[PDB]
Image (cartoon, rainbow, N blue to C red):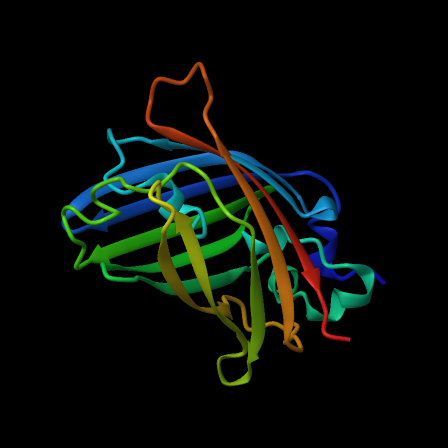
Amino acid sequence: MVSKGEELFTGVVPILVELDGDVNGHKFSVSGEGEGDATYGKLTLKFICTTGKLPVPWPTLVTTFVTCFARYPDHMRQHDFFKSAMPEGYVQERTIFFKDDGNYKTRAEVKFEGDTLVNRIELKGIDFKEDGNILGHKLEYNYNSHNVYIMADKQKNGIKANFKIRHNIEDGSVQLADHYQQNTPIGDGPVLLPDNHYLSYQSALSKDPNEKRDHMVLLEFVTAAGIT
């Protein structure tokens, strides 16, 4: 049997992303469009800064900008919280601590609006150094592969994770971004609370050569792996 959640992701699904941000008082908005194909764990998205020049590096927003598109292998299907919460969706919240710098706090609602999977996000950043790696745009426009360990959060009826993102800097060092995450369902319907498992991410950042606005093109693959 294919679950109600699973069935919404069997083909290619349009994605809309909307982010309102404020970092050290610098307000900005970003809109993204593209498509997800969960069968292949595949996301393609193009993000546009709709208010001017982005005041933080595009790589710092990659994790913020739809884990329902992860590929869960057949043997792992009982651990897919994210699809099980659909179509009503889930709230994803994070704090992201940039080592020796500021932090982001994010809240997103991920849910269907008709046939479109929407990721609506608010982001607030505080305590950034005006000449640190973030406000000083010292990060390379690239992205490393990362594994994220997903744990059930029984009390909140959802999941949680903590993971470290490494953002490469041109002197060979990295800027660490320590993510703490909680997800909880929007509906009061049944969800899958998983056993501990990993999601394996790879992400590629590029540019649309014909786009004059400040923007990012993201290609991301996400696959679950178990602990058996």
